[PDB]
Image: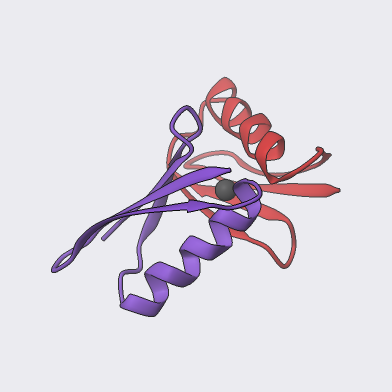
Chain colours: A purple, B red
Amino acid sequence: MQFKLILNGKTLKGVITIEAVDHAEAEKFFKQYANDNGVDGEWTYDEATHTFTVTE
Amino acid sequence: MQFKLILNGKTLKGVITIEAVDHAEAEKFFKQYANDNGVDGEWTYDEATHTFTVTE
Ligand code: NI
């Protein structure tokens, strides 16, 4: 299902949409996306939006 | 499966194990647990242990 992640970092801004199976898959997938492109921070999650964000 | 919650709060420390259906309902049980018992802070998640943390 549709899960979204907002990469609100220093240099880069972003919004990614995926169709992962659940909160579990979407979560690890986004931990790895943010890590691979160099934004790491605290993760916020709204379950009304199915939207993760990571803020630096 | 057994999901865990590490409550790192100013005064209170805690560790809860529950048997919620998935990462989703465990995380919401832990969200409404955290406010219901009055800890507000930053959440990190370990997928090796099935273990949430909130550090106030
Ligand atoms: Ni999560």
Determine whether, in the image, residue A42 is placed left or right of residue B12: left
| Residue B28 picture location, percent across and down | 62, 32
Determine whether, in the image, residue A27 is placed left or right of residue B22: left
From the image, which quarter does the N terminus of chain A lie in?
top right
Between A54 and A2, which is closer to the camera in this rendering?
Answer: A2
Q: Give residue A8's quadrant in the image.
A: bottom left
Q: Give residue B48's quadrant in the image.
A: bottom right
- State how many labels appear: 0
| Residue A55 picture location, percent across and down | 29, 55
From the image, which quarter does the C terminus of chain A lie in?
bottom left
Vertically, is A42 above or below A36?
above
Residue at figure coordinates x 59%, y 25% from the top left: B32
Q: Give residue B45's quadrant in the image.
A: bottom right
Between B8 and A39, which is closer to the camera in this rendering?
Answer: A39
Determine whether, in the image, residue A33 is placed left or right of residue B49: left
Q: Residue furthest top?
A: B36
| Residue B52 picture location, percent across and down | 63, 51
Residue at figure coordinates x 22%, y 61% from the top left: A9
| Residue A14 picture location, percent across and down | 25, 57
Residue at figure coordinates x 57%, y 63% from the top left: A28
Vertically, is B36 above or below A8?
above
Q: Which residue lies furthest to the left in this view?
A: A11
